[PDB]
Length: 589
Image 1 (tube, helix red, strand yellow):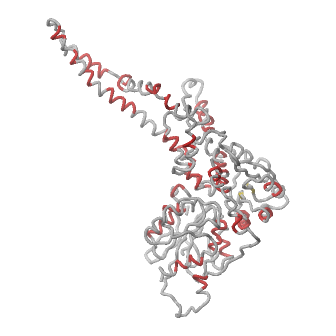
Image 2 (cartoon, one colour):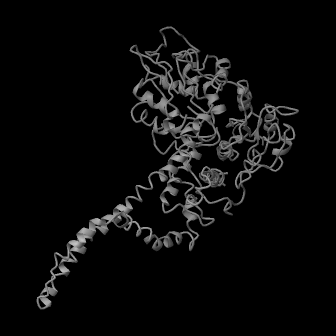
Image 3 (cartoon, one colour):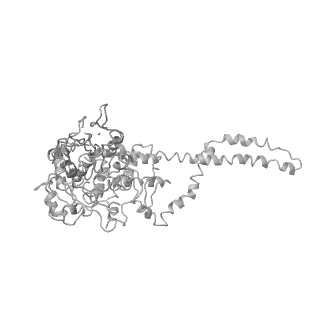
């Protein structure tokens, strides 16, 4: 079953019906913020959402309730929350955007509908005088010269016509549109009641439409549609105490599930495999045996995609990043503290994750663990640098080459599927690789391994560690530029996010107008479409763009890796340096 991916989404009821408790807990505010006199002039605060389960809509604009659906596709199939805490900035306040764009650009429709209803009431108002003037001069030929006359019996109108007030010149054209709405809200409540086939486009709207941030208010049905059929997405508890995993009720809404609950890192391995979920949501320190080993004690048995909750202390940057070599995929950026109004958002950083972490069949497990083969360390860059680390450095076999590095990153899949790619960057070859990823000190313990393990030194980006001899790397508020001398460095970028993410796309787009031909860009495993509209121009001209399915897990960054054609081919992961050094062979020489 593969449509189960769409079934593995809409835990996607929590992002949906989530801000309705931002109406009863935010309109009962516009209430006793008023006093004992403002008691009968504040309720008409339309509980605006979208209900096929029950009767409830937005006052007229079904577009803005679909426009808030042209939005949740990318916000979930690109994973904006399960990464860095700054990646969700223009997103909790862009909820209020479309909210206050319908609370902001929905009286440019009202006032302009009493405008369009004023013009017609005053486009036939020339034809009431023209149907009064031409009505007062025909008994003048009928009657036996009965005079009274028309014109002096006419300027009573043109007096009254402009003696009119907005109650007749703006509100009488207004006492009609919503009066004609009594002749309209039938067929707006007949489209979805006398028919059950509005969910047919809606339950089919979970696979189209594009935007990008968090303004889904309550689109895809209230809590309980029985169409949540067959098998849901369960997820096992593992936190250090009782309250930590409203953190047990983070899932108990109508999507992702809880199954097992245990403080012990041993009563979990004796729990997550009993009543199979699809992810064990687990942490660092566990009583009797540790969470560092509470995954490989369950991996060397049942490699379940583990959700590593890690409230880092700057030393947990290894528990979060050694357990990736033990079997992690995407890690939660575990918090804790002020229980207020953010748990509504703090859950999408967890449940949308498994709606992206539990988005795996048995592929990643059955990729190097079908038998008893441990991958090991590194081979040798045969097609490139090994042919140099095996012959004569003298002018016999030398190359007319240049020393300009080729750049490039990733995210979910950075932990291991990107690490096996960087561990073969030879010191004999002057290069520089991009890494911009999902994480706070994790940029100082994710390049520390390629530094020590791989036989070359890669660094954490400071205020300009110009690079080739090491590596760019580090997503840390992170524009490498050119002086007047010929090469590049490592400079930072920190405005409002490029593509609303905190920003893989910008540093790829920069290089199309910065260094060129001896420059490469590559895509591996994340979930964003950034490296699709950015390196689009590097291959729309001259600059190689580089994933295939067999190696990694969830594909949302390589999901649209063939809709463009700028990519040369496909490419899974094993010994990438054999080729990613062969791209610095013919265009640098």
